[PDB]
Image: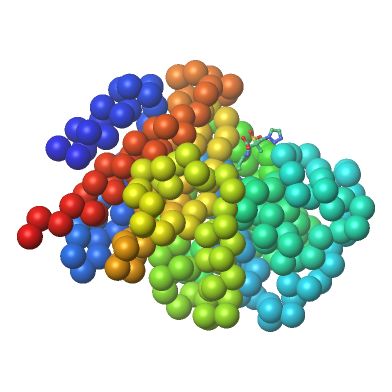
Amino acid sequence: DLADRFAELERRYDARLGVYVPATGTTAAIEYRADERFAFCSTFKAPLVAAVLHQNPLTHLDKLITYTSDDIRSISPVAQQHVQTGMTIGQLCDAAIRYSDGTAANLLLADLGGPGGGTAAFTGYLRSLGDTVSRLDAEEPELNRDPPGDERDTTTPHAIALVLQQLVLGNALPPDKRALLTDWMARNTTGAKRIRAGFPADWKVIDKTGTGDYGRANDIAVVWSPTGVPYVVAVMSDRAGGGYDAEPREALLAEAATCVAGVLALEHH
Ligand SMILES: *C(=O)/C=C\N[C@@H](C(=O)O)[C@](C)(Cn1ccnn1)[SH](=O)=O
């Protein structure tokens, strides 16, 4: 019946919708097109920050990276502000997560794998985490621009949640480093209208959004019940019918998250 609720969202928003919530002790897994591929968009910036965190000591976050206005080829609200003084690796992670800064993400890719191998290196951190399905093939902004049906720069709701689960609720990062990722996602500025909107205020939410062409809108989150019970939420969508310039629908994601919140919070004693 929840599948039918999701189907209606799709009909109404003229859109394809992907949802995954892993099973916990107390709940079943929520799945709707969980193994269909969806463009990553900026959602990759979360596991990217984990990858830089993991490969280096915390000292590495103080490394000043300089770049130029030449390097800014995508929306970079923080990297623009710091073009002349440079940004540190920590600042970059800050911007990548909290502002979805494209330049910031492209520098972390270079830090991770050098020039020319950052995508390979990021995909390999996911492989190290037992995700064989996901893949990153390009930098910003081109990763946001592949056609529907192209496997390049795709993940699936299933895969990316299971990765986020490991990153936030598992040991893929130690506590000093995991906390920093969580603090950055917790302080996200781009996600108020997606998973966050679908959940009561006394549930805690950390998240990383995505947005892109063909009406792509993503959100991945980790949510906490008022009594600290955690869940992973992956919600992904596109709207290929409108062409490359089609309107993405944040409302579609908030509705989905509301269905999920509905399930996870109603207690049936
Ligand atoms: C961020 O999560 C993923 C994509 N961001 C896009 C967006 O914010 O809509 C762009 C990178 C925006 N853009 C236009 C020109 N340069 N950047 S994507 O639409 O290209």
Q: Residue furthest right?
A: 84
Front-lying residue, 18 or 13: 13
Residue 119, quarter of picture: bottom right
Q: Position of residue 268 (x, y in %)?
A: 10, 55
Q: Is residue 229 above or below residue 144?
A: below
Residue 198, quarter of picture: top left
Q: Position of residue 30 (x, y in %)?
A: 25, 50
Please state, as top left, top right, bottom left or bottom right, where the C terminus lies in the image: bottom left
Q: Residue furthest top?
A: 242
Q: Is residue 2 left or right of residue 94?
A: left
Q: Residue at x 29, y 68 (%)?
A: 227
Q: Position of residue 94 (x, y in %)?
A: 67, 60
Residue 60, quarter of picture: bottom right
Q: Is residue 209 left or right of residue 222?
A: right
Q: Is residue 269 left or right of residue 180?
A: left
Q: Is residue 25 left or right of residue 76?
A: left
- Residue 151 in view here: no
Q: Position of residue 217 (x, y in %)?
A: 49, 37
Front-lying residue, 209 or 19: 209
Q: Residue at x 27, y 42 (%)?
A: 259
Q: Residue furthest front?
A: 202
Q: How is the image coloured?
A: rainbow
Q: Residue at x 45, y 51 (%)?
A: 220
Please state, as top left, top right, bottom left or bottom right, where the N terminus lies in the image: top left
Q: Residue at x 31, y 29 (%)?
A: 9
Front-lying residue, 90 or 140: 90
Q: Quadrant of ligand 1?
A: top right
All told, the count of numbered labels is 0
- Residue 264 in view here: yes
Q: Is residue 142 above or below residue 106?
A: above
